[PDB]
Image (cartoon, each protein chain N blue to C red):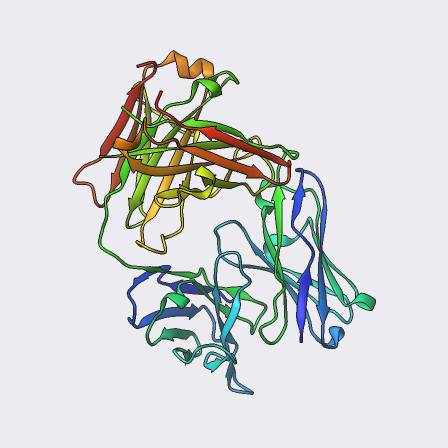
Length: 218
Length: 210
């Protein structure tokens, strides 16, 4: 199998910066007889089909803006955006098609901004909810950058595991931040077994971790 | 105008089978081999294999040997992808993509879930204790999507409605949050308006301090 290593997997950029994505073939995709490289680049936007940008490593698809070009030969290929615009915020994939198909891991492009600490809020279950035997505890991480954040759930100091799901918004189109919910799911009987529900948040922008907590019933 | 048009989104119980349709158009169907690509929620593109559209022969990626089958109905210029015995890991979008050029189908989303159609329960995320957070827990509904608005649309600034998640039960769940000024709690009324068109259900919930 021809393997495809794409890098970097993520790129944070400003209006007008030049952007470079590198692909690496485990075997050459230069077919000697016709001297063509069997290599393509795709841009894919959320909920959309992939869109062919460049094929034969360097030929641009009709309709692709001029600022995209592909180059390289054999095992090493590069996609260049001379000057990136918000239109280009997408995920990019390389594709070898000499010997079957192999897609790269993909490269995500985000808007860079200054670091921003999240605003943390904790939300206890509602009395309405407890009537059905399940208790949902919700931790909100509001308007932070970059995406990386560690959320730790602590019930009566006891570290939770296996019983929470997170959700992240897409990078905000006006202030370039992300937001994260974390939801701890407990049974009504476990929820009332304990007192102190804590959410502990780690992020680049916080001097040290931040805990938001509440006491069941108080 | 060449195009591939795939069949609609599919909601299926574990263990069941799904046959996805890809209808080609605007060229000689038999001259071009067809490819199938899998994309799991949030993940990269995975080539599953290829079918010879003249002779019918399939070739499978090493990870899709067993439970997957490509076939044709060349009379109708259609490629089929069948998944037998659906697992959680088959939840993904499936694309057909033709050899040579830029042509892809629009993709068929496949959800695997124990759930049947069910509308949400909505619970207040009540404000705390100069800006406060508050919101709505939209829980235990199926399938996607729900729409959430705040004060019949009057309140859009500071709103975050998160992407849904599949719980272990196979039911979706999300939260809608808003940051508002502390000083407005007890003055201003905050109502979240949840709509779920599949179950044909609509729910408003006032969210006030406890």
